């Protein structure tokens, strides 16, 4: 059954693109990654980097998570990210997202062995 580490890949990794190509990016990715299966997930970040480089974050700058846990790590460098946010016209099963492209540091929580990301905490 899906692992938290496979689930982070599915929801958050798009190594296949450098950046989101059009205003549609979010709509199609949210749908194709099955993030809008039971309802419209309202925020979701995709990261346009190699999996190894996002796994490395687990050994970068250790920081508190937004919720106060201390297994959160912030990337030493900025990454190319797409921010996806639900719009006023979103309506399940027709979930609708704003596509914002950015270059920011990313903060994830890590677990397990190998010690890998399993939640996207924030971009900064
Ligand atoms: N900038 C952000 C903020 C939040 N999240 C996702 O939105 C969720 C609820 O706020 C977070 O938990 C995270 O999901 P996940 O934990 O599945 O990585 C995200 O992807 N990007």
Image: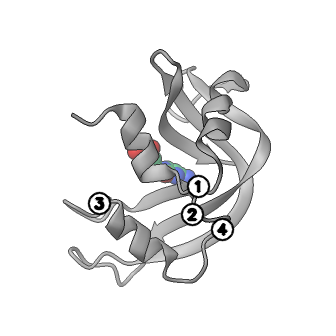
Q: Is residue 71 above or below residue 124?
A: above
Q: Which residue is mark 3?
A: 34
Distance between the alpha carbons at the discs numbered 1 and 3: 18 Å
Q: Which residue is mark 2?
A: 83
Give residue 90's quadrant in the image.
bottom left
| Name of the residue lying farthest toward the front | 16
Instruction: Determine if the C-beta at disc 2 is less than 8 A from ligand 1.
Output: yes
Distance between the alpha carbons at the discs numbered 2 and 1: 15 Å
Q: Which residue is mark 1?
A: 15
Q: Nearer the viewer, residue 91 or 105?
A: 105
Query: Quadrant location of the N terminus?
Result: top left
Q: Tell me the SS state at disc 2.
A: strand
Q: Tell me the SS state at disc 3.
A: loop
| Residue at image coords 28%, 64% | 36
Distance between the alpha carbons at the discs numbered 3 and 4: 20 Å
Q: Tell me the SS state at disc 4.
A: loop
Relative to residue 96, is residue 109 drawn left or right?
right
Q: Tell me the SS state at disc 1.
A: loop
Give residue 112's quadrant in the image.
top left
Q: Which residue is mark 4?
A: 19
The answer to whether the residues at label 4 and label 1 have Cβ atoms under 8 Å apart is no
């Amino acid at each position: 059954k899906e692992t938290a580490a496979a689930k982070f890949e599915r929801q958050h990794m798009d190594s296949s693109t450098s950046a989101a190509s059009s205003s549609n990016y979010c709509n199609q990715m949210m749908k194709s990654r099955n993030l809008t299966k039971d309802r419209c997930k309202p925020v979701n970040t995709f990261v346009h980097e190699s999996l190894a480089d996002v796994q490395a974050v687990c050994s970068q700058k250790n920081v508190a998570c937004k919720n106060g846990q201390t297994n959160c790590y912030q990337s030493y460098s900025t990454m190319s990210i797409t921010d996806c946010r639900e719009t006023g016209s979103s309506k399940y099963p027709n979930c609708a997202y704003k596509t914002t492209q950015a270059n920011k540091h990313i903060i994830v929580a890590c677990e397990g062995n190998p010690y890998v990301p399993v939640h996207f905490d924030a971009s900064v």
